Image (cartoon, rainbow, N blue to C red; front, side, top):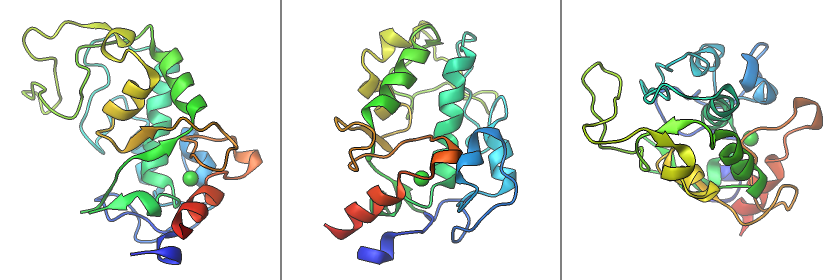
Length: 199
Ligand SMILES: [Cl-]
C-alpha cells in the first residue's frame, strides 16, 4: 500500500464516504472540508450533537465542559470523518494511527480545555456503560482536564485512542497536520499527506 495509492482517499470506517468528493453543504465546524470531503452532510451535523451518535460517547460525563473546549472536540471529529488527507496514517474496518498534529493544534486544544472536567486519563476503555452512554466508573473523581491530561500531548493522544500524535513540529513546517483551518486559506494538510506518501 503506497504512493499515490494513499492520497485523496477515505478510510474504510463505518461512516466514511467511499471516496472523497465536494459537498455543497457541510455543517459549521466541518465547513473547511467542503471542497473535498470524506463526510456527508448528515455526518457533519451528527458531529455537532450534544452526544454524537457517530460514537455514542459523551463528552459531558463530568457535567462541566466549556464551550471553547467542546469546540475543539467537534473540530477533531470533522477532521477524522471529513479529511481526504489521512491516507498515509490509515492502518487495518480501517482506522488511523498517530496522525501527527501540529504543536499549536494540541497546545490550543489543551489550553482551552484546562478549566473543563473529566474523570479518566485514558478514554479508550473502562467506562461504565449502563445508559448506552458512558459514565464515570465508581471511584473515578471528576477533576480538571489539566489533572488527567498533564500535557497537550496527553490530551491529543489519549482522547482519540492514538488516532493522533502530538507532533513536535509546528504549523506550516510541512511535517504536521492541522485538525482545523480557516476555509479561506486553503487546506494546508494536502501538502503534508503528499510528502509522507512519498518517503
Ligand atoms: Cl485535511
